[PDB]
Image: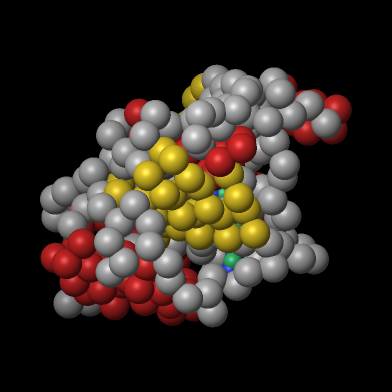
Amino acid sequence: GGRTLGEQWKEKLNAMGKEEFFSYRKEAILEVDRTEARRARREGNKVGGHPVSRGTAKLRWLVERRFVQPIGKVVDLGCGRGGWSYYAATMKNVQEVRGYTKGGPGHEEPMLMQSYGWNIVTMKSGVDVFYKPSEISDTLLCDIGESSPSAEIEEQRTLRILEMVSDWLSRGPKEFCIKILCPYMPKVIEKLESLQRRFGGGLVRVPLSRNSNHEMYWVSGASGNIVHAVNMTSQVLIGRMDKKIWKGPKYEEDVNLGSGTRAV
Ligand SMILES: CN1CN([C@@H]2O[C@H](COP(=O)(O)OP(=O)(O)OP(=O)(O)O)[C@@H](O)[C@H]2O)c2nc(N)[nH]c(=O)c21
Ligand SMILES: Nc1ncnc2c1ncn2[C@@H]1O[C@H](CSCC[C@H](N)C(=O)O)[C@@H](O)[C@H]1O
């Protein structure tokens, strides 16, 4: 009963001043150096192995730790420029990648790249996934979740995604990676515990995430108590607040996606 630890985190966050907030945001997080990829983007370099976004490094973190092992037909919901879609197209047992994203003004259009296995990637823009009828996949990825200063608004947004994701999961995919925008709210916990009982997996925090969000990833390769996993992350995020001296992020090399087509 009562307020959850994550709720205290969000309140404290919302109570920070401008200066404190931006220092906190990146404190002791993992960050990939995107310098080379940004210069590649503006040079139109499609063959250098540079990921289209920071999302590639996030998925890389999870896959290298076996939290998800993409296979067969991969469906990527909210693919954006295609960071997750392209990364999956480099996996050994992936046969097809299908991405869906809304695109349009203010939102990311899929980028056409020549990273390894690009020829098995098909991203369709102009697609609102909440109105897209589910399809069969072997791997389901979903990276949707728009932040709000309101934990109530984020709760509802998370619950809408989980309802949507549940429909795609009943379709059979045994591998999955689903962004949980607001995992600390009681209603979201209850749904997650229900979905874990049916579909398995567990919640993991990726350290590449900023301290200004509590996003966790529901992944098939994880297991264990959801509440404990969430509270631990709440503790780490709160412990990083009001620091004496800011250490900032730990920088890491970006993912290399290579080039070339793969056999079909
Ligand atoms: C700009 N913000 C954002 N913010 C809190 O941090 C949360 C995430 O905001 P953010 O850091 O802008 O991340 P996001 O919106 O995802 O931006 P991006 O898409 O660049 O990742 C908000 O929901 C809000 O609770 C803030 N809290 C305080 N105290 N002061 C601030 O200036 C801000
Ligand atoms: N209802 C919806 N239908 C389809 N796409 C949506 C959507 N709501 C948000 N999105 C999109 O989902 C994306 C989430 S960011 C996705 C990043 C991607 N994983 C990568 O690695 O590059 C945004 O581009 C946003 O435009």
The front one of 217 and 72 is: 72
- Is the residue 97 above or below the residue 125 in the image? above
Q: Quadrant of ligand 2?
A: bottom right
Question: How many labels were placed on the picture?
Answer: 0
Is residue 54 left or right of 232 when viewed as pictured?
right
Q: How is the image coloured?
A: secondary structure
The front one of 190 and 214 is: 190
Residue at x 31% of width, y 42% of height: 68
Seen from this angle, which residue lies furthest front? 264
- Is the residue 189 above or below the residue 121 in the image? below
Q: Residue 194, located in which quarter of the rendered image?
A: bottom left
Residue at x 51% of width, y 47% of height: 97
Residue 129 at what x, y percent from top left?
A: 54, 71
Residue at x 18% of width, y 57% of height: 200
Quadrant housing the N terminus: bottom left
- Is the residue 198 above or below the residue 225 in the image? below
Q: Residue 23, located in which quarter of the rendered image?
A: top right
Residue 10 at what x, y percent from top left?
A: 44, 63
Residue 150 at what x, y percent from top left?
A: 50, 74
- Is the residue 132 above or below the residue 214 in the image? below
Is residue 154 left or right of 190 when viewed as pictured?
right
Asked whether residue 49 is in view, the answer is yes
Is residue 64 left or right of 57 when viewed as pictured?
left
Residue 38 at what x, y percent from top left?
A: 75, 31
Residue at x 38% of width, y 62% of height: 136
Asked whether residue 26 is in view, the answer is no
The front one of 232 and 169 is: 169
